[PDB]
Image (cartoon, rainbow, N blue to C red; front, side, top):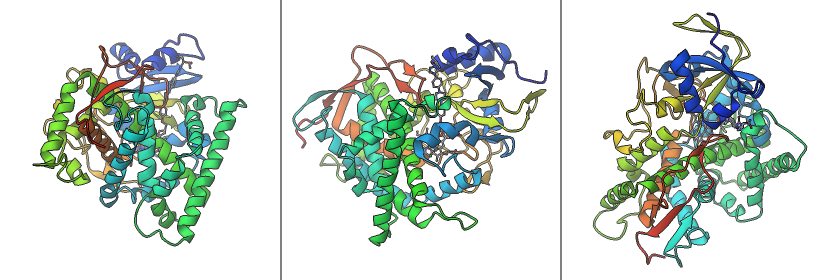
Length: 484
Ligand SMILES: CC[C@@H]([C@H](C)O)n1ncn(-c2ccc(N3CCN(c4ccc(OC[C@@H]5CO[C@@](Cn6cncn6)(c6ccc(F)cc6F)C5)cc4)CC3)cc2)c1=O
Ligand code: HEM
């Protein structure tokens, strides 16, 4: 009566890892139907306490700074991958402000600039890459698991870092990111640093990529032109001063960029991968977006005026599509807080011993039939003339709160929380809809793809983000054959 019911573990230290590791939303539901909303289950030595539904969103995201802590849970996943000093390798208050700094490059004025850039890179890929080669080919097959992470990393790189850094990638140093990218695996949670080639190439890579950003930060500064609020590198050059007057070192700034680049790239890659495969099973939907985009362009020329950020606003169908994939495949299937003081689940007789791991999964409610009718059908129409990414789209108090990076909703009690809530809330929400929006609109305008006498592959949950199975590929044709 004082603790949540810990459950059976197939092999004990191993715990429920396979059932949960194989499918969390299924595993969660099986327990719910005979224990209720909260229950514990052990995993890799660490036992896991879960709270399902909106109320579990409140108890976790809105937990006091003293009761839980995300630094503890994420430290080894990120630090060895990004670097020291920043993001979970520092007090919470340092993290909060590092958000404030970064947000200055994620504003409406930046976004208007980012869209043409982001589109321009996509068009580079359509031509130069073997997957498409639109200039010479009219048919094609694209492995979305290859293309999307490359398109996402090139688009993010160009928007947030600039054109000098995007030209540096055209080289072998591209490799260094593949090596650091491999370092970013849930295998870190338990194995942070081992002596085999993987971990060495990963530490080496980090230090060389950190140097690359340090040198560009250096020159961009001394050269003396950091004036346009061009990007994320500019905004950290001018804002990197904490409350107390302490100032981030340039290596620390460099590690933050790496953190944010890889952080944003993985999540956004999944979602673009997923709405390509899903849009491919239902090509009817692609033509909905295509008609809407052409009607917006108006009378002649494929586009009367190349599509802008403001225009991206006027396209509910594009935005509704992004909301549906984030519902059906929230890249982050489970979010953790390590418990630092015993917690008294209210409207309950439970204490969560200190030292347990607290797991919240908005994705469950997203996939849940208890909260969405026909939850496993890809139907973006369910968003009824409501294309907003977020608002207090659910109940309880939704008044505002400031944790040090801008005022944010107090109430997190919604079934749909793809970007989370509370202090660790995502700051990249609007950058994603822009980036993904531009990828989507650029894709349908030039290509019409399909899905090979089949339907969407089963998701793999064994990595950072929820990704598709190995033979994941779309077969494209051209909506207009002659353009160069
Ligand atoms: C079946 C055999 C079995 C045995 C074991 O072999 N087995 N096999 C396989 N598995 C297996 C494999 C994996 C798991 N994982 C459980 C834990 N999951 C996970 C996912 C995401 C996480 O997020 C980390 C942070 C959160 O915020 C981010 C992200 N972000 C938000 N916006 C942008 N980025 C962030 C923030 C800000 C930044 F600036 C940067 C950032 F990055 C980073 C944390 C944890 C992964 C799956 C479980 C089981 C097994 O159990
Ligand atoms: C669809 C794409 C994205 C999704 C679904 C997403 C989702 C989330 C979620 C759920 C969290 C909360 C994690 C937690 O509570 O522990 C989060 C945090 C965060 N995200 Fe994102 N994110 C996305 C893209 C981005 C991008 C593009 C950036 C940067 C440009 C970004 C930066 C962050 C940061 C800095 C945090 C805060 C980490 C913390 O407070 O501990 N995310 N994101």
